Image 1: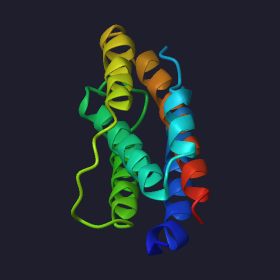
Image 2: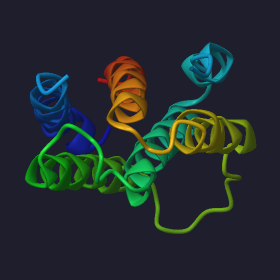
Image 3: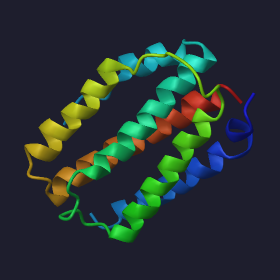
Image 4: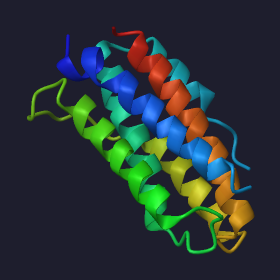
Amino acid sequence: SCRWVDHKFRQHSETSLDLLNTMANNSTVAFPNDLYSQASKASAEDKLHFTVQVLEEAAALFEEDHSNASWEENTVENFVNVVNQQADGLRSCTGSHGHKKKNKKLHMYFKRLSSHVLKKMSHSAEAWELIRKEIRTHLMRADQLVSSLR
């Protein structure tokens, strides 16, 4: 049982989703259900490890050029800051020392959003709207995984 899961995660999720909604008002690759299915029936620690990776992968997409996105930069800054806070918060639910592997298939999936949506579509406003929709789904499914541990 973790301060962050019990007192902070829901409020950060709601804020992160409000910011994506603000982004969406200015306007693919199969959702990785098999990876979420495995996380769903995994240990609490393995569910947290998975969820931290989802959040950090989602934040890492905004290292890509989003100059052509329909959003304000301040909104992107606020959204990535909240996601970064959420990741750090869930990381705090386990010990600082460990050996767990990064999920390779999840990493490959986020690389395929980078290559097959953003890079193929030259980082267009339309490409970023597709990424926004997928990120929102990740955040909703992440909130489901965390809520199972309350």
